[PDB]
Image (spheres, coloured by chain):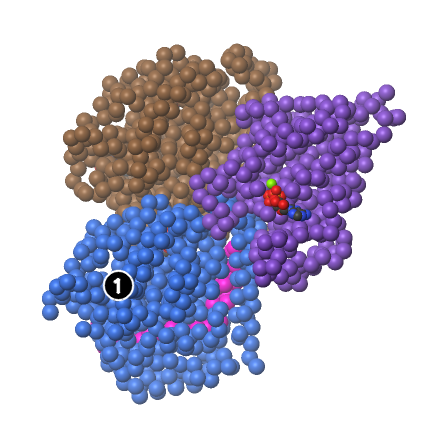
Chain colours: A brown, B blue, C purple
Amino acid sequence: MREIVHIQAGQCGNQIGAKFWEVISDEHGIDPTGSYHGDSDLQLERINVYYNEAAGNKYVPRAILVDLEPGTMDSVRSGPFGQIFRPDNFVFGQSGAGNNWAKGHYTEGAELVDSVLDVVRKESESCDCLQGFQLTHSLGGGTGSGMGTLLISKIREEYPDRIMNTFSVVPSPKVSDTVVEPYNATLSVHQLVENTDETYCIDNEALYDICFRTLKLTTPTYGDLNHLVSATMSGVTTCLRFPGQLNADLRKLAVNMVPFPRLHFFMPGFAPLTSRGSQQYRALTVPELTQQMFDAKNMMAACDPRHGRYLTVAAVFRGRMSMKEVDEQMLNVQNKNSSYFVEWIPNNVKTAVCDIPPRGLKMSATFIGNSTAIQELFKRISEQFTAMFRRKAFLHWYTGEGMDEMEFTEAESNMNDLVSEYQQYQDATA
Amino acid sequence: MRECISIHVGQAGVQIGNACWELYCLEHGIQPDGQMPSDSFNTFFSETGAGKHVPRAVFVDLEPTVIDEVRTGTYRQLFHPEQLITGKEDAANNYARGHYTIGKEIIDLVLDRIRKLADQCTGLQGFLVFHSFGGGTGSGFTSLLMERLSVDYGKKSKLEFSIYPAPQVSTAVVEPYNSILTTHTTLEHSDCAFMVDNEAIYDICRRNLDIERPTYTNLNRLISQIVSSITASLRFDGALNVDLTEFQTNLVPYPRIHFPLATYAPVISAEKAYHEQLSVAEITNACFEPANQMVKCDPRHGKYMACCLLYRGDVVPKDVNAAIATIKTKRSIQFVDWCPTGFKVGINYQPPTVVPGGDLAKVQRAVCMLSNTTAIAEAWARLDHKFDLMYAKRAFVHWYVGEGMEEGEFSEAREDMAALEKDYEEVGVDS
Amino acid sequence: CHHMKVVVRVRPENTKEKAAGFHKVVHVVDKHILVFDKDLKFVFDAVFDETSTQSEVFEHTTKPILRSFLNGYNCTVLAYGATGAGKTHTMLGSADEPGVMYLTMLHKEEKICSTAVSYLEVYNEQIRDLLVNSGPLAVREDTQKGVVVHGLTLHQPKSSEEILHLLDNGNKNRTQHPTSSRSHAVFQIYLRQQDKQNVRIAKMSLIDLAGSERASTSGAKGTRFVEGTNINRSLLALGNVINALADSKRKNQHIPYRNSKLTRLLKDSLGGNCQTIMIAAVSPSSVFYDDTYNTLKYANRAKDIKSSLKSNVL
Ligand SMILES: CC(=O)O[C@H]1C(=O)[C@@]2(C)[C@H]([C@H](OC(=O)c3ccccc3)[C@]3(O)C[C@H](OC(=O)[C@H](O)[C@@H](NC(=O)c4ccccc4)c4ccccc4)C(C)=C1C3(C)C)[C@]1(OC(C)=O)CO[C@@H]1C[C@@H]2O
Ligand SMILES: Nc1nc2c(ncn2[C@@H]2O[C@H](COP(=O)(O)OP(=O)(O)OP(=O)(O)O)[C@@H](O)[C@H]2O)c(=O)[nH]1
Ligand SMILES: Nc1nc2c(ncn2[C@@H]2O[C@H](COP(=O)(O)OP(=O)(O)O)[C@@H](O)[C@H]2O)c(=O)[nH]1
Ligand SMILES: Nc1ncnc2c1ncn2[C@@H]1O[C@H](COP(=O)(O)OP(=O)(O)O)[C@@H](O)[C@H]1O
Ligand SMILES: [Mg+2]
Ligand SMILES: [Mg+2]
């Protein structure tokens, strides 16, 4: 019925996609070889949302592997759960963007886009009722950001009535992993604002903070961060695969969480998260999940929701619970924090309950918050861009691929307008 | 004889209907697979072939999850396969999607199935429609379906069992839009509309039954008890019988005021059952308590217009008369000036049945009340204020506009609701 | 200087509907007062009816704007009406020739006047050039200037019939009922006044909007519906911008221009920097009933108070 096509571009996108597919395959009981060895019928009841049935009791994920360099997907293929993917969906070039948005959007991506779109069309026509797409990438690299934005624009042109989801790793506020991340981030937000239905913003620094403070992990690696992102993705898409007492798909969340077209940048979160030693000292109840969800330190983006006001909030519970408890918890949260929710929207919180819990835990929840405190990320990126752009530093790398300064000015002005809108919608005027 | 067709649309309607049909099969001795192991139950079932009973129901939804749950569950062999109708993509909390875009590909199929069901009928007198205001498919497809049925049938009564939005408790952000739009469209196509509030059911379950975790099953069981009490006059014989026409001719004084409130008594747990000698006067009195009301509104803020009392079990007419006279002489509850005789009483014989695993005791007598009161004007005012707040800045409007709805429909619906508010305020002035 | 004039052109009754058992829901009194049906009171500057011909609306539509469109940023004439009212007829049949081919001869003693014109349409949230066959164009913003359509074609007629040739070729390339759901056609005139001084910036903007459709109640699915509802969302964005440009004393704030390509083109023309006048068309029949009195009519009251500026004689 409602089915999803997955696309991942670049090094970070590829790694997050690999972790996410291992997670989902273990959730639906599919071995590395692709055969089914589960123990419930609900696992195979809605397998078609993410998988294609192959010959001989085999399941092939509906994923596209895109990269401008071959090493990352070579490692992905040679690793575990690397034989589960269809080899024809590995689409790679040979040159690479080199941390250049122009190279990934106008020089190499302009050459790989035809092949990637042919693969995407072949995957999408075989769908029975396409629900939407889903892109995993970042905003600080060349191939990831540039090719992801190009693919998003092309898909929006081809399929304008569908749902486009993005899980983009926005640049970190404190330490920068690339000298030219402001340029790429601005030029990619310029396209995300227009061509994306809803965008989930995640920061690596917030993930480190979660892994060091809540999980008490002494030495967190990128595997843990990809694990957290995979958990968030599965929690977001859980209602399409399992029955529930009150269910909401992607389009319902988009309708309930996006009041105006240009405001679709959310911050995600997960609960419960605890250390190994502290699990004996806590009780898993709906109030505890609700308390942990609405925590500043639990957010997956480096923004503090207490600096602004929530527009809308979505919580997707999983497990066996009572709707009365969930509803009174939402009411209590709304009434206690009346200064942190917008006045001109009553009942800021949307709710959904899924019957089947994550493997292991008996309870879980997912948080999606559309807050006006996300303007700080855009404001910081705009400040860095306009500081580096007056001196025209590192600009010739971008203008040697045909890009002209009018595009930079347009992107900066669009980002400034988005910041102004988010700031202005903190005023009730009533 | 005389039969009734039940229509369940949306997730709320489908689940409520599942509970109601489990209760109905339990009442008449029908096994979950339809067979009778051992004939006044044909007003809801039909004899097919060699001793199989098929309910006269149609299950409609725009997504396959809950209808598939029904198709796989223990009652998979009770319903006709073609009566569980399923779409592909739900309305996603959008009135425009359900009414204009997604409902138009299965409306013809649903109407054809309804016609096929009613043709087999020989004394059809009404439809029962279960839905919720806040949903997308619920509100939209219910409005479209009632418009089509009113065009097609016209004289047959059309009752409603809807889930009114709660004053504070909510599970969606765009609820006021859908509620206002569906009310505006449906106001001229429904003969009656009984409503309950989920928040009030939570309160009743927490207080009366002493349950701290009342999932949707308990609410659906309470609503099933209400519907069973309403239709027992049809299915069983009694001292006084009430049809589907008497409800509309007694509870609806004006064509735009057809929103009664449904309560039930006694809702008690088996711990307090052994210590209480429940009798006609006590349950009749309990039907009037503001805390026992099943919609989150205070009847003391308005004036009663017409009340229907449905007794079943070990109930004597003289005790009913005495209890009603006692209620009438009470000065704390008010009736409108132009309704000197405002009671309709029906007395049945079959006591309410107990569903194993339920949270209710076994009682020898029970009461179901349906009352028309002006205390719902406050609920209308609250809904209109929410609509006005969310609409002044045109929030979420683009979602509806992109699915085929013009901007004028919001203004039309708001003006219609204002007119309804003025009508409710004018009907309650003494003269 | 500030009054955004709103004129209502009451269309003559349709020939097929006139005798088919309908009444008139719009009653005309004179050129200053109008009455609806219930019995609502409406005043919209000048009011026209079936008696006035195509050229008879010139007296209160474009003539006391285009006296000499140099002292101000001047014309931003829109055309509401929705389907079947006659906005496209009124604009593109006659009442655009009074603008040019009828007001190209205006004196030369104090100035030397030359013009530059361009034509574009907005279809499916994309911009196309109607005079030359070119693909979608990109709108670029900047602090110094306004919005500029990257790739538009500029033309400088040096006579009068050149404008009629350009206009005639600008309508056969419009997406003409694949009248029905269509594209918003924008005509831009640039006035040059080289002195025989540097007071030469003026631009005249003429817009012929599309109509809002109800789809399922009156319309279709597939195409004519995907190409539809883009008109609806663009009109919603335009209405939001208009409402935000005339709200009480707050005004200012943040006006959501970027929600559509149509409103971006009007960033420098819908705000208060020019003398602008609106035209709306309404059908007096009762078959439409509701769509004739809504943001078609209620909203134009809110756009009679769009305070503007004209001191910038540039
Ligand atoms: C003693 C014990 O049994 O521990 C559990 C466990 O549940 C705990 C400790 C887990 C554990 O998680 C971690 O320790 C962890 C470390 C780094 C990064 C992220 C997590 C666990 O890994 C998590 C894992 O849970 C799952 O398997 C979930 O289904 C999870 N899937 C995976 O983790 C997974 C990993 C590889 C391959 C396939 C699946 C999941 C979560 C969300 C959505 C879908 C699936 C299990 C049972 C445990 C350990 C092993 C310690 C916790 O995590 C989650 C996601 O539930 C830590 O905070 C919770 C608290 C839990 O009690
Ligand atoms: N009493 C009761 N109410 C329910 C039940 N299920 C859903 N609801 C109500 O329905 C509201 C949510 O909207 P739905 O009725 O589920 O909408 P829908 O029918 O699924 O249609 P969509 O909006 O397209 O998903 C909630 O606010 C609940 O109050 C139920 O089983 N019992
Ligand atoms: N070479 C390369 N580097 C990237 C790309 N995208 C992002 N990066 C950089 O990689 C950093 C983190 O990415 P990564 O560690 O792979 O993401 P994670 O493992 O999921 O947390 C970011 O700060 C980016 O600067 C890309 O496409 N190619
Ligand atoms: N003053 C008028 N006299 C006669 N017919 C008119 C008048 N104004 C408009 N019409 C008719 O109304 C119709 C409206 O169509 P048109 O203006 O081309 O597109 P739209 O319906 O989108 O405005 C035209 O076909 C035209 O014949
Ligand atoms: Mg549903
Ligand atoms: Mg036209």
Q: How crowded is mark 1: few (under 14 residues within 10 Å), some or many (20 or more)?
A: many
- Which residue appears at 32% of the width and 29% of the height? A123
Tell me the subunit letter for badge 1.
B
Farthest residue, direction right = C109
Q: Where is residue A368, by image quadrant?
A: top left
In the visual, does C83 lie left or right of A202? right
Q: Quadrant of the C terminus of chain B?
A: bottom right
Farthest residue, direction left = B37
Between A291 and C235, which is closer to the camera in this rendering?
C235
Residue A174 locus on image (x, y percent):
47, 25
Q: Can residue B34 be seen in this view?
A: yes
Q: Which amino acid does label 1 sit on?
A: Arg
Residue B428 locus on image (x, y percent):
53, 75
Placement of B120 over or under C261, stated as above or below: below
- Which residue appears at 59% of the width and 38% of the height? C256
- Which residue appears at 75% of the width and 23% of the height? C158
Between C310 and A207, which is closer to the camera in this rendering?
C310
Between A406 and A263, which is closer to the camera in this rendering?
A406
Location of ligand 6 given as a quarter of the image? top right
Placement of A311 over or under A403, stated as above or below: below
Decide if ligand 2 comes within 8 Å of the CB at mark 1: no
The residue segment tinted magenta is: B362-387
- Which residue appears at 28% of the width and 60% of the height? B116
The stretch drawn in magenta includes residue B379:
yes
In the visual, does B338 lie left or right of B210? right
The stretch drawn in magenta includes residue C209:
no
Residue A118 locus on image (x, y percent):
36, 24
Residue B169 locus on image (x, y percent):
42, 56
In the visual, does B431 lie left or right of A24? right
User: Residue under circle 1?
Assistant: B56
